[PDB]
Amino acid sequence: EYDYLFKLLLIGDSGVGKSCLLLRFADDTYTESYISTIGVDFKIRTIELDGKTIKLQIWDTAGQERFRDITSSYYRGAHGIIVVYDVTDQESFNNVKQWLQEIDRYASENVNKLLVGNKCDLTTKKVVDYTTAKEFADSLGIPFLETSAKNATNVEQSFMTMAAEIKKRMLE
Ligand SMILES: Nc1nc2c(ncn2[C@@H]2O[C@H](COP(=O)(O)OP(=O)(O)O)[C@@H](O)[C@H]2O)c(=O)[nH]1
Ligand SMILES: [Mg+2]
């Protein structure tokens, strides 16, 4: 059982590692093989926060951003949305603004937001500096972390940070 159930969604440009982030967190696996669908709509991981048991239900886009678009209902039912970009791809960071506008168009009014810059292991290809993305996130009052699904860097922390934000909003 659990004290709380939080529904999370990862959004962002195709191929930034959203599915790899989910699979690393929920299953502790990583592959470079191409992923269209993960065989389920969501994965589950149960965490502990402040002595409370929190079931996290984390939904995958099923690659719908590859050739079409994310449906509005996927936005509306989330308690928190993680916007992911690829630190080696300037365009994916530029498009974070558009993903935030989609959240404003379709998500719940009080949804929690978190910015993640993934593939932080690719040091020689990195083009979005930590300071650039942190300044942007700070300007919106949204938390920000850099992650590596491949090396597991900050992946658990990213989901724990989102859970902490949601719990704080729920208790207020
Ligand atoms: N180097 C590195 N590559 C990654 C990482 N996460 C994902 N990738 C690569 O990015 C590709 C696309 O990841 P995927 O999870 O399918 O992206 P999605 O379309 O956003 O769900 C993968 O096949 C990996 O090659 C990471 O943390 N580091
Ligand atoms: Mg995917």
Image: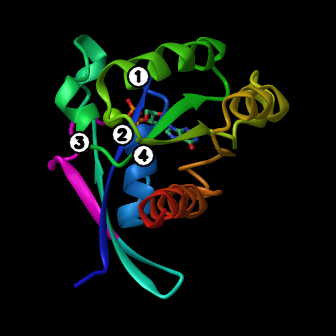
Q: Which residues are magenta?
A: 32-45
Q: Which residue is mark 4?
A: 20
Quarter the N terminus occupies: bottom left
**CB of mark 1 within 8 Å of CB of mark 4?**
no
Distance CA(mark 1)–CA(mark 4): 25 Å
Question: Would residue 108 appear left or right of 115 to someone viewing this image?
Answer: left
Mark 1 or 4, closer to the camera: 1
Q: Which residue is mark 3?
A: 77
The extreme bottom residue here reads 51
Examine the structure image and report whether residue 126 is included in the region drawn in magenta.
Answer: no
Nearest to the observer: residue 50 or residue 98: 50
Question: Would residue 102 appear left or right of 128 to someone viewing this image?
Answer: left
Q: Secondary structure at mark 3?
A: loop
Q: Which residue is mark 2?
A: 33
| Label whose residue precedes the other's in the sequence (1 or 4) | 4
Numbered label attached to residue 104: 1
Name the residue rendered at 78%, 36% in the picture.
123
Distance CA(mark 4)–CA(mark 2): 10 Å
| Label whose residue precedes the other's in the sequence (3 or 4) | 4
Residue 22 location, x and y as percent? 39, 51
